[PDB]
Length: 72
Ligand SMILES: [Zn+2]
Ligand SMILES: [Zn+2]
Ligand SMILES: [Zn+2]
Ligand SMILES: [Zn+2]
Ligand SMILES: [Zn+2]
Image (cartoon, rainbow, N blue to C red; front, side, top):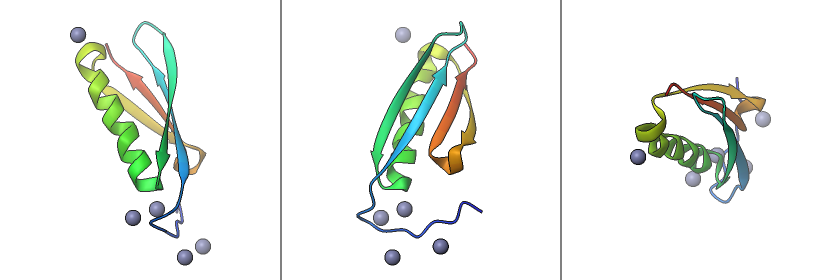
């Protein structure tokens, strides 16, 4: 699954849709290789944990969309 031919110079966009405990939202985009952009997206979620609580992710669109929810 999620078949991927890697290239160091590949350029993709990972879209992170965030939903917070009070229902508020925001979307953040990360660009670079599929691997690096994905790592950056999760790193951003981690930076938001102190104020927003632990997060849960549901991967969509073959990995190009990360739906992340914060517990509060
Ligand atoms: Zn190739
Ligand atoms: Zn192939
Ligand atoms: Zn790759
Ligand atoms: Zn690489
Ligand atoms: Zn704070």
